[PDB]
Amino acid sequence: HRVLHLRDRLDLAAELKLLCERGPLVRIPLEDGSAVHWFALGYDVVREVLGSEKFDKRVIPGNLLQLDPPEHTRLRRMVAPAYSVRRMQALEPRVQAIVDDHLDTMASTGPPVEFLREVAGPMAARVACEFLGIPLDDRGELIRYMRELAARLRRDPGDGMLGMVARDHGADISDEELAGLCAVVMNSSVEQTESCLAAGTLLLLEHPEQFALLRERPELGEQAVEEIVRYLSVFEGLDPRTATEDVEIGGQVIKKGEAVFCSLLAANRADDGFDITRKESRHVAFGHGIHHCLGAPLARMELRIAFTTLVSRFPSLRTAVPAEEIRFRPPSSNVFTLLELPLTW
Ligand code: HEM
């Protein structure tokens, strides 16, 4: 369903805008008759689908996204406390210092920099290691095996999320499951986070009035992050939800066995101007329901710290090429991202 990923730079492509005019829930019978699929394109309908207990994540270790209740509930309940408010507050100054480390490197290497590979990527990966409690001597290689690392950490719990889980649920979670929890954080989550960091920096640079506003008013940081994750929608479309029974959604009956594809991109953008003064953003960039992004507290905190510090430390920041020359990854189910971001200051 490639149409759900068609963009014009950061915006929706005409072809996808045209599809969204067909309504927030679109029936898509397959040309071969093999199945009936649905596109959930609107904010309310996507929330209706994702909140419903009448869908599973069937195909048509430690990876929560591939589990349905009750097994999903069991594992999520064990890892959830690592993202409490009390955990993020204790972590914030250390995240601030990691951000500062990387903007230190940047300000000393001097311009230009390829912001994605040289700053955003390493920063996100280093924050993830800190959150997970990866031993310092393992971080270089991990960022550059998983079962071995997870088994050693399980043998002697340390700090961070992996230590909490092993300490508090040692017997209940296997080596491979603990390794899987680590991999999801270090792989997909870093991809999404680094993309937000780099493309969000571009978005701010393309709205210089708001780049400056966030420097003058750092208290806008939390609002800015919500507007940035809404506007970017780097996680564009979700794994299909298959109805386990007939269910009425947005006025239509989705029959047992039919698959629904939620487009966070369309839900976040099809209604929109980028504005960090918005006090509350209408978006589903982190999903909704039992699979709602477990990392959202961390992502929100890391991005707030990163964007606020960046605009403060680099008021002269600018793209080293015309914005219109930036390359974006072509339509794919993979995370949306630019390919490189040359900056100068
Ligand atoms: C801006 C960055 C991020 C975005 C936009 C994002 C987005 C999402 C979305 C939309 C989902 C739901 C997928 C679905 O329901 O099919 C999800 C799930 C998940 N995310 Fe994130 N994510 C981000 C960063 C992170 C981080 C930093 C972590 C961990 C440190 C993380 C860990 C997870 C996990 C474990 C799940 C699965 C939860 C479950 O299935 O119960 N994500 N994310």
Image: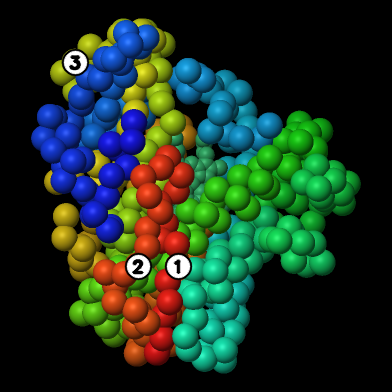
Estimate the x, y position of residue 202 in percent, counting from the top left: 34, 70
- Does the numbered disc 2 mark a residue whose Cβ is under 8 Å from ligand 1? no
Q: Work out whether residue 320 can be spotted.
A: yes
For residue 69, side relative to residue 28 (left or right): right
Marks 2/3: CA–CA distance: 41 Å
Vertical order, 333 against 213 (above or below): above
- Local crowd size for mark 1, using a 10 Å CA cut-off: few (<14), some (14–19), many (≥20): some
Mark closest to the chain's N terminus, 1 or 2: 2
Secondary structure beneath label 3: strand
Amino acid marked by disc 3: Gln
Q: Where residue 326 is drawn, which disc sits there?
A: 2
Vertical order, 75 against 132 (above or below): above
Q: Nearer the viewer, mark 2 or mark 3?
A: 2
Estimate the x, y position of residue 194 in percent, counting from the top left: 49, 61
Which residue is tagged 1? 340
For residue 273, side relative to residue 311 (left or right): left
Q: Pick whichever, 57 or 318, lies toward us.
A: 318
Marks 1/2: CA–CA distance: 7 Å
Q: Are the residues tagged 3 and 1 within 8 Å (C-beta)?
A: no
Question: The N terminus is located in which quarter?
Answer: top left
Q: How is the image coloured?
A: rainbow
Question: The C terminus is located in which quarter?
Answer: bottom left
Which residue is painted at 45% across and 62% down in the image? 339
Which residue is tagged 3? 252
Marks 3/1: CA–CA distance: 43 Å
Q: Are the residues tagged 1 and 2 within 8 Å (C-beta)?
A: yes
Question: Residue 76 lies in what quarter of the image?
Answer: top right
